[PDB]
Image 1 (cartoon, rainbow, N blue to C red):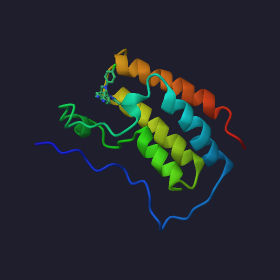
Image 2: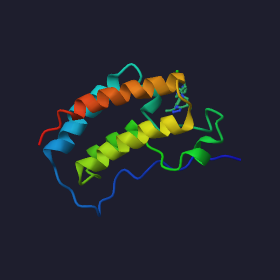
Image 3: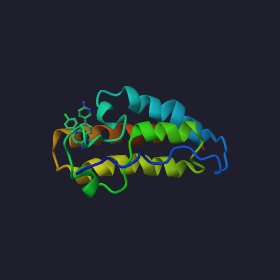
Image 4: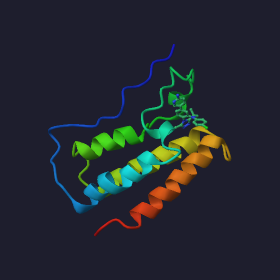
Length: 126
Ligand SMILES: Cc1nnc2n1-c1ccc(-c3ccc(N)nc3)cc1N(c1ccc(Cl)cc1)C[C@@H]2C
């Protein structure tokens, strides 16, 4: 049998909280732009491998990540360093490349989201 894992942790009241220009930009600008993109929908929540009848997804992907979880981490002040968020976006993209194969439709879609991501963080405030 196959059960999805629990989503990644998103909120923990023991972790200290800080508001930074970079974390606010990642929420208010970057996540916003990726979220309306044409290709955002597969990435807006955890991959539901039970629904999709994919029992190997979580055999292959051991560090799940998605924009819904990133949104939550940002808005719940889970991240301390901006690079924690940028690492979660890279995990999301790379999970797609790992599970799938070069040139697959969803890989082309992830590649385009990644290109938008990189253009947006080029303008990360200091
Ligand atoms: C992210 C990610 N990384 N690999 C996958 N995905 C993926 C995640 C969710 C879904 C999906 C599929 C149907 C639905 N109703 N909601 C979400 C499809 C995906 N994939 C997908 C395949 C083709 C296209 Cl055009 C879009 C998404 C395939 C595969 C499971």
